[PDB]
Length: 162
Length: 162
Length: 162
Ligand SMILES: O=c1ccn([C@H]2C[C@H](O)[C@@H](COP(=O)(O)NP(=O)(O)OP(=O)(O)O)O2)c(=O)[nH]1
Ligand SMILES: O=c1ccn([C@H]2C[C@H](O)[C@@H](COP(=O)(O)NP(=O)(O)OP(=O)(O)O)O2)c(=O)[nH]1
Ligand SMILES: O=c1ccn([C@H]2C[C@H](O)[C@@H](COP(=O)(O)NP(=O)(O)OP(=O)(O)O)O2)c(=O)[nH]1
Ligand SMILES: [Mg+2]
Ligand SMILES: [Mg+2]
Ligand SMILES: [Mg+2]
Image (spheres, chains in turn cyan, green, blue):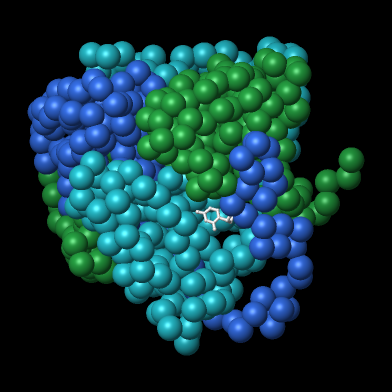
C-alpha cells in the first residue's frame, strides 16, 4: 500500500465495473502503456464487418487528460482485427460505458470474440486544452518561417510513389 | 477574459481560417480532448474509397508539441468512416492546410460528407523530441532486464488466436 | 555537442540497429513529432492484404513513456497504405524489434515496399501509469455531474447520419 517515492505523482482513475463478472483492466507487464479492456460480449465479425462492443467499464478520465483506446498488436497481425475510430478518444467528461468499434480487416476469415477476451487497450495521457487564437496569417502572429513550411503528405519522400 | 487560476498554464494555438465560412473548431463539451474539424467540401465516398479532404484551417502547433487528427466515434460506428493515416500527425513546423484522409470502411453504403459537417477532431499534446543514443546492445547501455523482454504481438494471450 | 538551454530537458532513447545497413530513424524537419522508421525488407501487398514488417531497430522507451507507431500521411493518401493496429503501442519494457503491421486499404493497386523505404513514424510521449480506483458509482466517488454525461458515439451531431 506504500506509494514508492518514484510513483508519488501517479494518477488515479475512477472505474465502475458495469459488468462485475469481468476482471479489472490491467497492464500485462510493468511499465506497459495501457490496461487491457475486456469484451463483455460474444460477437462474430465476418470479413469487412464492424461491431460496437461493450467493455463492461466506465471511467472518469481526469480533467486535463484523455483516455485513448488502441488496438492490440497480436490480434491485428494474426486475424486482422482493428478499431474503426482508432485511437478512440475518451473525453474527461464521459461517464458512459467504454465501447470499442471493432472491425475485421481480413478479406476471408471471420473473427470470433468471446466474452472475457482482451480486445483493446486503454491509455491515459495529458492533453492540451487549446485556446485558439485566430490570426489573419502566421506572419501577423509574428511567427518565424519554418523548415517544413506547407510541406506535408509525403513531401519528404522515402517511397517511389511520393 | 479572465484566465482562471486553474487554466493559467493552458496553451494557445494560432489558427488561420483559410475558409472563413466555417466556424472555428470547438470542443463539444468542457474537458473534451479535441476540437472538431469541419469539412470545407462536399465529397461522396463509395465503399472502400478514400479522399483527401480540406478542413479550411491551418494551425501552428507549438514546438515541443504535436497535433493529432482522430476520427469521430459516431461516424465510425454508424457509417464506417475512418481515417487512413489515423492518428494524423501534425508537426509543429507545419503551416499548410490541415487535410483529412477519409476512407469508407463500409462494404456497401456510400458516405456523403457535406461542407460544414464535423468529420474529425484535433488534439494537441506534448511530444518528446527524442535524442537517439545508438548502443550495441541494451546490456551495454547497462539497462536492466525487463518483465516484457522481447514479448510482443499477442505474447500476453487473451484470445484463442494468440 | 552543446545541449541548448532550450533542450536541456530532452529525452534520450537508446536504440539498437538490428539491421546496421539502414540509417538511424530521423525527423524530416526540426520540430517534427516523430522519427521515420525504415523497412528492413521488400514486401508486396495486394489489395486488402497485411504484412508484419521488420524495421531493423529495437528501442528502450523510458519507463513512464510510450512509443507510438503512426502511419505516414503521403503513403496513406497516395496508395492507401495503413497500419492495422495504428497507433502501434510500444511499451517501455519492450526490448524486441519494432515491427509494423502494414495493410493495403486500396481496392485495386498493390503496394510495393522496398528495403530502405520510410514506412511509418515513431513518436515518444509521456503516459500516465494509471492506478485504478474501483467505485460503485461516480456519485460515491463524489464526482460532479458533467456536461457530456454518458453522451458519446455522435451525440453532439455534425452529420446527417447522427
Ligand atoms: O492527417 C494529417 C497528417 C499530416 N498532415 C500534414 C501536416 C504534417 O506535418 C504533414 C506530414 O505528415 P506525416 O509526416 O505524418 N506524413 P509524411 O511523412 O508522408 O509527409 P512528410 O514527408 O511531409 O513528412 O502533413 C495533415 O494535414 N493531416
Ligand atoms: O506497432 C507495434 C505495436 C507493438 N509492437 C510490440 C511492442 C509492444 O510493447 C508489444 C505489445 O504491443 P500490444 O500490447 O499493443 N499488443 P498485444 O497486447 O497483442 O501484445 P502483448 O500481449 O505482448 O501485450 O508489441 C511492435 O513491435 N509494433
Ligand atoms: O472508442 C471510443 C471513443 C469514444 N467513446 C465515447 C467516449 C467519448 O467521450 C465519446 C465521444 O467520442 P468522440 O468525440 O471521439 N466521437 P463523436 O464526436 O462522434 O461523439 P460526440 O458527438 O458525443 O462527441 O464517445 C467510446 O466509448 N469509445
Ligand atoms: Mg499488450
Ligand atoms: Mg466528439
Ligand atoms: Mg513525415
